[PDB]
Image 1 (cartoon, rainbow, N blue to C red):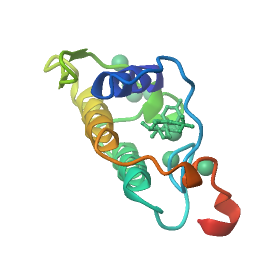
Image 2 (cartoon, rainbow, N blue to C red; image 1 turned 180 degrees about the vertical axis):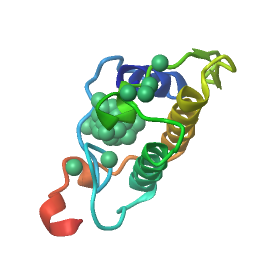
Image 3 (cartoon, rainbow, N blue to C red; image 1 turned 135 degrees about the horizontal axis):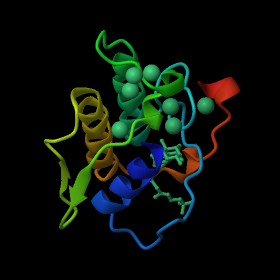
Image 4 (cartoon, rainbow, N blue to C red; image 1 turned 30 degrees about the vertical axis):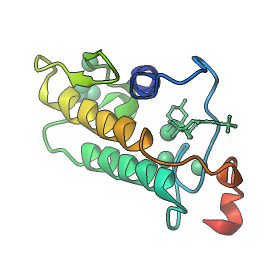
Length: 124
Ligand SMILES: C[C@H](CCC(=O)NCCS(=O)(=O)O)[C@H]1CC[C@H]2[C@@H]3[C@H](O)C[C@@H]4C[C@H](O)CC[C@]4(C)[C@H]3CC[C@]12C
Ligand SMILES: [Ca+2]
Ligand SMILES: [Ca+2]
Ligand SMILES: [Ca+2]
Ligand SMILES: [Cl-]
Ligand SMILES: [Cl-]
Ligand SMILES: [Cl-]
Ligand SMILES: [Cl-]
């Protein structure tokens, strides 16, 4: 679920700001997306969006109001290591994996302050 993704991210990135409140970034980090990702971090978000897009196409899964973000799962965090619980059902596991891949991806990408709150209407 969305609130778990936020924690999972703070797990992969211990950081120095807990609920620092995430702002939109680039062309895909945020609700929706359009055009082409502008950088590494943005690509991480596009991949995530595409993973959720795949989720919506699972013949065996149908989420509340068709939003994968509503699907709660179970995961654990260690020294920045993320592990999706094997007891998650198939639909939950697919979502947990999308989130885990993204958290790791985010933790490796540079943060270009010039892309924060980008004017998506013109550059995306
Ligand atoms: C982990 C990433 C970096 C955080 C960061 O270093 N911010 C520093 C800002 S500043 O330089 O201090 O201004 C941030 C960049 C944009 C963030 C995303 C956007 O805020 C959009 C989404 C917001 C939702 O609450 C959580 C998922 C959601 C999809 C966020 C995942 C975390 C992202 C991908
Ligand atoms: Ca998005
Ligand atoms: Ca269902
Ligand atoms: Ca669930
Ligand atoms: Cl989002
Ligand atoms: Cl958007
Ligand atoms: Cl369901
Ligand atoms: Cl349903």
